Image (cartoon, helix red, strand yellow):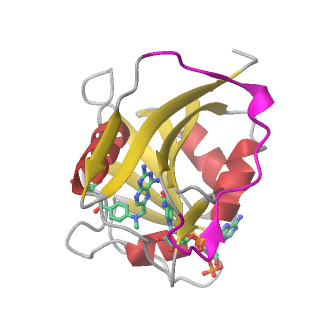
């Protein structure tokens, strides 16, 4: 059972501004949905684990994230009536429930700085799929401080991408104990 982190950070390490995203990148978001949705074993599902403010920053039409199992960490949210969503009061309990479910193939840590930090300290930590966006978007939330020395960066050829006047590039990292 793998836990991969997926994030889009800017030149300063920013991920959030004013409770929302500092940018909108539809092609990047499409790649995000593909990476987080597609499983190898047909019929098996992925799980996304997110913090409450991520959940609330998703457009409610796209919410819950379709074809995935949503786990929202929150100490304040009421239980979610929907079946593809569960509210988990702690990281450890969320990870316990996920490793308990048989049909979950890969757990995608999709955001919340604290969610990211707890994942980075997790035994299930596998890969980081980072989208390095160029420039300073005046973010107020950031990605955790991470020791990249624990990781091996994939060497595949990664071109630059540009949409909406914004440039960015994909990077992949794998924990060195694999
Ligand atoms: N650029 C990106 O790739 C990216 C990735 C994700 C999000 N974002 C942006 O980043 C910002 C949100 O990230 P955030 O870090 O500010 O808020 P968040 O982490 O998304 O959600 C924070 C909330 O999650 C809950 N939570 C987190 N860890 C928990 C734990 N261990 N146990 C229990 N509850 C826990 C708490 O909810 P309660 O307050 O209800 O306890 C906490 O207040 C938004 O702007 C979002 O759009 C961007
Ligand atoms: C605010 N937020 C958090 C968020 C945004 N961008 C990211 N970008 C990356 N690279 N990684 C992340 N974890 C990430 N997280 C959002 C907002 C909307 C949707 C969303 O609606 N996704 C659709 C896909 C949207 C699309 O196809 O354009 C899906 O079904 O997955 C996801 C995350």
Find the magenta span and give its range.
Answer: 136-156
**Percent x, y for residue 103?**
40, 33
Farthest residue in the left direction? 61
**Percent x, y for residue 131?**
46, 45
Where is ligand 2, by quadrant?
A: bottom left
**Percent x, y for residue 125?**
67, 34
Query: Where 152 falls versus 117 (above or below)?
Result: above
- Which quarter of the rendered picture does the C terminus lie within? top right
Task: Work out whether residue 67 can be spotted.
Answer: no
The residue sitting at 65% across, 53% down in the picture is 116
Tell me where residue 75 sits by quadrant.
bottom right
Task: Work out whether residue 70 can be spotted.
Answer: yes
Residue 158 lies in the magenta-colored region = no
Side of 2 where 159 appears, left or right = left
Residue 147 lies in the magenta-colored region = yes
Q: Between 128 and 27, which is closer to the camera in this rendering? A: 27
């Amino acid at each position: 059972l793998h836990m991969n982190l997926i994030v889009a950070v800017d030149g300063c390490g920013g991920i959030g501004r004013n409770g929302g995203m500092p940018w909108f990148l539809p092609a990047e978001m499409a790649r995000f949905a593909k990476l987080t949705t597609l499983t190898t074993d047909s019929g098996k599902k992925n799980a996304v684990i997110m913090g409450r403010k991520v959940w609330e920053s998703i457009p409610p039409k796209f919410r819950p994230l379709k074809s995935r199992f949503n786990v929202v960490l929150s100490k304040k949210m009421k239980e979610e009536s929907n079946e593809n969503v569960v509210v988990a009061r702690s990281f450890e309990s969320a990870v316990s429930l996920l490793q308990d479910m048989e049909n979950i193939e890969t757990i995608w840590n999709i955001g919340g700085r604290e969610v990211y930090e707890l994942g980075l300290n997790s035994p299930f930590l596998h890969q980081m799929y980072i989208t390095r966006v160029e420039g300073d978007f005046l973010a107020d939330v950031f990605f955790p401080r991470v020791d990249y020395g624990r990781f091996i960066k994939s060497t595949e050829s990664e071109e630059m991408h540009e949409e909406k006047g914004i440039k960015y590039r994909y990077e992949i990292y794998t924990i060195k104990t694999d």
